[PDB]
Length: 128
Ligand SMILES: C=CC[C@@H]1/C=C(\C)C[C@H](C)C[C@H](OC)[C@H]2O[C@@](O)(C(=O)C(=O)N3CCCC[C@H]3C(=O)O[C@H](/C(C)=C/[C@@H]3CC[C@@H](O)[C@H](OC)C3)[C@H](C)[C@@H](O)CC1=O)[C@H](C)C[C@@H]2OC
Image 1 (cartoon, rainbow, N blue to C red):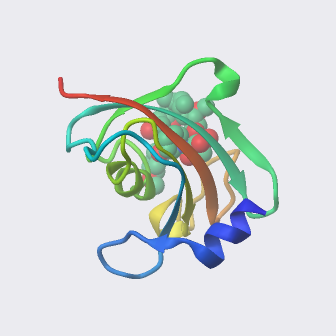
Image 2: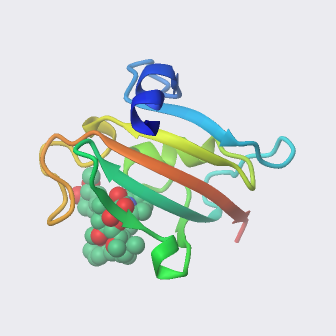
C-alpha cells in the first residue's frame, strides 16, 4: 500500500541524505513557487502508524492545520517536507523517528521509535 510504496520508491528530501524523510508527489500543485520560512501555511493531513492504525486526520475536524513554516512549530519532517510543496500539492511523507517523535513518542497517539506516514495537502501559504 501507500506506506510501502513511499518507503521503497520515495525521494530522500533531507539535506543530510540520511533517508530520514522520503517523499512522493501524489497530486501536482500550481506553478513553481513553494512557501518561504515564516509563511503561514494551511494544510490538510492524515497520519498512519507503521502498524496500519490511522492516528489523526484534519479532514475529520473540518478545519486545516495552520502553522508558521520553518520555526519548529511541527516535527522536523513537516518543516522539511512542507517547504518543498507547491500550492495545491498532495504528497506522501515517510518520517523516521529522528525527524518525528524519537524515543519519546507522543502520548497517547505515537509510540516510542515510530516511523510515521503522512498524506499532506498544501492548501495555501501566506506571508504575514
Ligand atoms: C500541547 C498542546 C496541544 C497541541 C495540540 C494542537 C494545537 C492540536 C493539533 C491539531 C495537534 C494534534 O491534535 C489533534 C495532534 O497531531 C498529531 O496527531 C499529528 O498528526 C502530528 O504529528 N502533528 C500535527 C500536525 C503537524 C505535525 C505534527 C506536529 O508536529 O504536531 C505538534 C506536536 C505534537 C509537536 C511536539 C511538541 C513537543 C516536542 O517535544 C515534540 O518534539 C519532537 C514535538 C503539535 C501541533 C504541537 O505543536 C501542539 C500541540 O500538541 C500528533 C501526533 C499529536 C497531536 O496532539 C498532541
